[PDB]
Length: 112
Image (cartoon, rainbow, N blue to C red; front, side, top):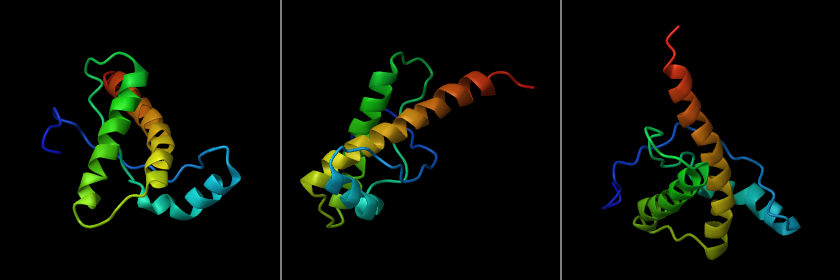
């Protein structure tokens, strides 16, 4: 727990997507430095929620407050640029993550 976190669950596993920062150099810089960013995202269970917006952005909030602290406490030091790029990343991650947390719920709750 990040010294707060009301129960937050970690993700599953996703990869490096191919972001669209809309600057040529940004698309290069990320293509090299993408490994700095997390391979999972922290979410809340779908068990009540409403609004994909807040699922993704509270996920992005916490995750960019977790994989900072988790690493920024070991003497890594995330650049400003990395932090803003990581936003696009963890946003597109947690989009796909909520597709699991909704579907694995709504389909898991079938049985046979």
